[PDB]
Image (cartoon, rainbow over the protein chains, first blue to last red):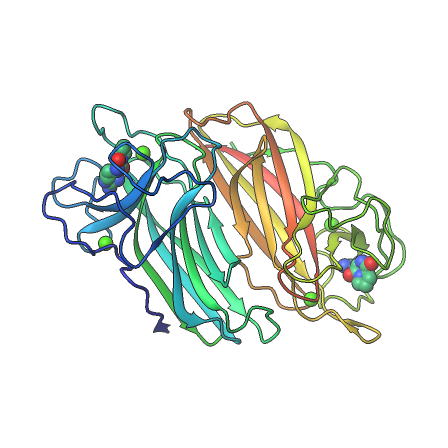
Length: 198
Length: 199
Ligand SMILES: NC(=[NH2+])NCCC[C@@H]1NC(=O)[C@H]2CCCN2C1=O
Ligand SMILES: NC(=[NH2+])NCCC[C@@H]1NC(=O)[C@H]2CCCN2C1=O
Ligand SMILES: [Ca+2]
Ligand SMILES: [Ca+2]
Ligand SMILES: [Ca+2]
Ligand SMILES: [Ca+2]
């Protein structure tokens, strides 16, 4: 049960001082997964965007602290449900190796409360993907029910056989806002990828 | 408390098949062919991609067990190379999505093994089980179980519909997909069941 290295796996970079303050730029170590061009290259608050947010004691968004450290990673899409998807992506250095089971865990948060007097009730759905090259090997497409104000752990597993056509391609992770619901924002934290024999 | 949503030919029993490991190459009655990359032709043969039903009984070269339910399984076989697209079965149901309800979808997924005379059936394409309302995938199991040649495992997809869901009163739907992400590129499905449950 060795760990596979992921950059900024808990969105802890950058440091944020004030509770509930946030950035609006792609977190360092991740890129913006943008297959439908929903997220513009330059962002401000109230644009479709992603970034990190500080979920500290006293937070108005949850009934608990961050799953890990201070920060969560978030994705907010302004477009109406059905316009497409967006999220975060990271290609890893680890490659797909035969006779190995991979375990990917990430916590997913449905923030509640109010932003600028706008209700954050509701949820867009999520998908967590494990990749080799650009093939999605296994994914959790929105299986967990997650109430306003709480986080849950999504798990995705996959076993690579010596037959696998994608052996030796680089592993990837995607964390996606599905935009199938409003309020259309969600949080992610504490990305873990563990590898093991069979 | 927990009700069944009726599904046509939910265990692929129609039509009846008499001989061991025999199969049809036509879309199973009650089901549609889900064909977003045109991988499956309208008229099918041995030499092409196809789907249909197959009998799994004593004698079977494909499984270390008998069919999960009744006599038959439903199968999808794709002849194109890995990465070419996906195909599968789809069924639009009578029922529509209701608020404050929890849906559970279960299906047995089969990895047939065996060797048909120099052609090995070892290996597996990958599968996806989808629950739909309208044209929207609410929840899906994308290839999360590991299934050895010759065995079946049960996939479960669950979804809770809240009052604010944009998709209420849309017709529920099911898709069973061959991902074409490995060879040998066939897999089987059985015993499809969908239940509803006050949240
Ligand atoms: N989601 C968090 N944990 N923190 C809030 C980050 C702020 C983030 N960015 C925005 O521009 C606003 C607009 C409405 C919703 N937002 C957001 O979710
Ligand atoms: N899967 C079953 N139990 N039975 C039917 C399998 C038939 C399926 N379709 C075909 O045309 C044959 C050609 C060779 C491999 N085939 C298949 O895999
Ligand atoms: Ca964190
Ligand atoms: Ca919410
Ligand atoms: Ca059956
Ligand atoms: Ca097989």
